[PDB]
Amino acid sequence: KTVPQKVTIAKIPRAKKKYVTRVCGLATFEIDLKEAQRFFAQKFSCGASVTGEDEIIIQGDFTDDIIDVIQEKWPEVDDDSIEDLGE
Ligand SMILES: [Mg+2]
Ligand SMILES: [Mg+2]
Ligand SMILES: [Mg+2]
Ligand SMILES: [Mg+2]
């Protein structure tokens, strides 16, 4: 319906690695993005930023393993509810 009248601002870091991994939709599971950002940063020892309403950016390509990491950390994310958009 009507899109909310609302302004958001976010700083987004320059990518220093060959890739960045963008994670969207954790908030639709009521996962707190600050908690998620902390987990990813500590888990991977790479930079992680909250960059959108429902969006986290991780420095590095973690697409081969991040689905299993997310599902282990937040097991409410069932197999039918998470996917790599590059595949
Ligand atoms: Mg991959
Ligand atoms: Mg692997
Ligand atoms: Mg899995
Ligand atoms: Mg798809």
Image (cartoon, helix red, strand yellow):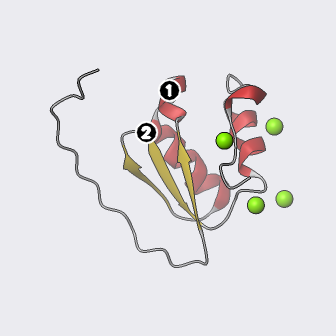
Residues marked 1 and 2 touching at CB (< 8 Å)? yes
User: Where is ligand 4, by quadrant?
Assistant: top right
Q: Is residue 56 above or below residue 25?
A: below
Q: Position of residue 61 (x, y in %)?
A: 67, 65
Q: For this rendering, which residue is in front, 72 or 61?
A: 61
Crowding at dot 1, Cα within 10 Å, few <14 / some 14-19 / many 20+, comes out as few
Vertical arrangement, residue 63 with respect to residue 81, above or below: below
As drawn, 27 above or below 61: above
Rate crowding at label 2 as few (under 14), some (14 to 19) or many (20 or more) other CA atoms within 10 Å: some
Residue closest to the eye, 54 or 36: 54
Question: Which numbered marker is on residue 54?
Answer: 2
Q: Disc 1 residue type?
A: Thr
Measure how far apart labels 1 and 2 are at the Cα level: 8 Å
Q: Residue 72 has which mark?
A: none
Q: Earlier in the sequence, mark 1 or mark 2?
A: 1
> Residue 80 placed where, x, y %?
74, 27
Q: Nearer the viewer, residue 84 or 21?
A: 84
Front-most of residues 3 and 54: 3
Q: Identify the residue shown where x is 51% and y is 79%.
A: 16
36 lies above or below 1: below
Image spot of residue 37 (x, y percent) = 50, 47
Which residue is labeled 1 in the image?
Answer: 28
Task: Look at 56% across and 47% down and name the residue there.
Answer: 23
Left or right of residue 7: residue 27: right
**Helix, strand or loop for disc 1:** helix
Q: Amino acid at mark 2?
A: Asp
